[PDB]
Amino acid sequence: EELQTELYEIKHQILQTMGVLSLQGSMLSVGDKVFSTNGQSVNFDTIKEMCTRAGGNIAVPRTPEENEAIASIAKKYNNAVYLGMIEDQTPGDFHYLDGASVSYTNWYPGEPRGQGKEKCVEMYTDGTWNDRGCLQYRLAVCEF
Amino acid sequence: EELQTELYEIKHQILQTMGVLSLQGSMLSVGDKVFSTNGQSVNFDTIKEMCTRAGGNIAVPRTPEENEAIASIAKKYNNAVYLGMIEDQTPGDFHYLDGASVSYTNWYPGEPRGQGKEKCVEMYTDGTWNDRGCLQYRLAVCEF
Amino acid sequence: EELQTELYEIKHQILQTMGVLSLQGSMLSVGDKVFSTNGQSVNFDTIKEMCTRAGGNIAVPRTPEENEAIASIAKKYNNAVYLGMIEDQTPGDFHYLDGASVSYTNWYPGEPRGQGKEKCVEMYTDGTWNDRGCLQYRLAVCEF
Ligand SMILES: [Ca+2]
Ligand SMILES: [Ca+2]
Ligand SMILES: [Ca+2]
Image (cartoon, rainbow over all chains, first blue to last red):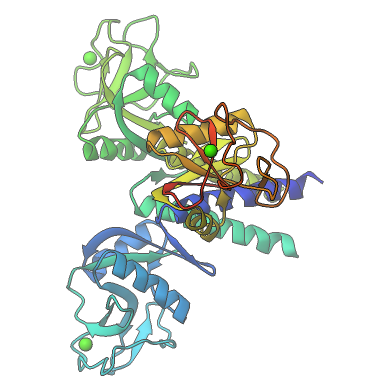
């Protein structure tokens, strides 16, 4: 049947485009998630908008492998990265932007300790996390 | 059935690739149209060939939103853009390259006024149009 | 039926992404093969890994048209390119990395003449081939 070989060509072409983007370092693929940056360092609200404009979301690692991918991008551009999570009303508790409680974490030892005054989360270039105010300039990393 | 979740993965991956290209400013998507440039400034015939070689066509805006997208690219590269239209045998009348009469227009006030000696159309960096000879160096913008 | 117009949109979007990558010189498409480089010059083993990490393979031309595409990339970056082939146990005989005997060739006159001491193959910037040791720094070109 012509349908499946049409699917074959389509799948092949998608893999070619993703292959080119990967080879050139334009993105990193981890499982079903693709991470990318525009190289800009801006505040949390600005990153959120940049990602959504491109049809994605501000990146958030939910597994060690995802964490290491974002860390490698932070390291490449030598700047910390704002992540897609924010502090609950209760200090020390963080949620994803959809409202769910954060599960996987990788806090730098002692963090989070902003006492409710640091509602955002940055990833240091070693991949560990720190709660931080949301107005700093951080590398914009999106997930798709 | 395995067919639709296969379609789901395919759709997701296409959105990832488009998301990366968009985030990095490699293209602009407006409805079903994608605009992109190679950053080169060359004449009308040269642009036509560059676009067709890449499987697209020299850009032409048919809506205000498309017009503003091309204008933003003109503004980014600080150069006017040749558009995909050319003057009819009768001065003042323009057609798309497929032969159809141009519908949406955004002429700079007083334009077109080349009296038949300016068969091409350039978009100024403010998005308005001017009829112009076809031999100038203009930013190559393609639509796909 | 909704399936085929869904396929239409998918095909269109793939062509847009490939069009953007092509227009910007990020890849070259020849038939069903896509060639791309990361611009790096490294040894044979390093190229192999870079290509496989991106989901492709070190490039190998099997037709004159494929050969000319890789040559154009060699010429663009002004460096010779390691190809996806290696010498058999018997000097002068080369195979693709899957083990099959090489068919199409484009040896520089007199080549291969490494007497079994040059197990890799480089493409000179004019597109002709030379057997060479595998430890030189050559442009990494992948096929997808
Ligand atoms: Ca803190
Ligand atoms: Ca004029
Ligand atoms: Ca030799």
